[PDB]
Length: 76
Image (cartoon, rainbow, N blue to C red):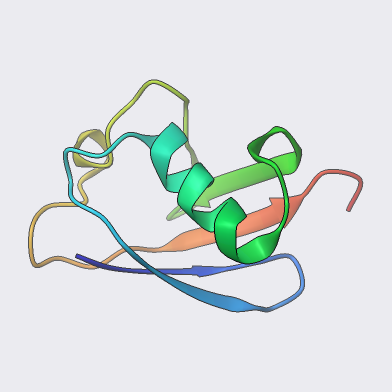
């Protein structure tokens, strides 16, 4: 799937993932692009706060669907 997330800084990051992938994994993939450890990340999906240990599927990110990720930095 094509994942798009906007950072606190308005930066668009594009990632590849499946519904089966975890939120934790998604954060790790973002880190590789953002440079910010998952510890400092606050990732929200369609206004709903994401929990670690969950899947993307659990939040209705199904195959060939879309995502609505809003990412903030801790301290911001």
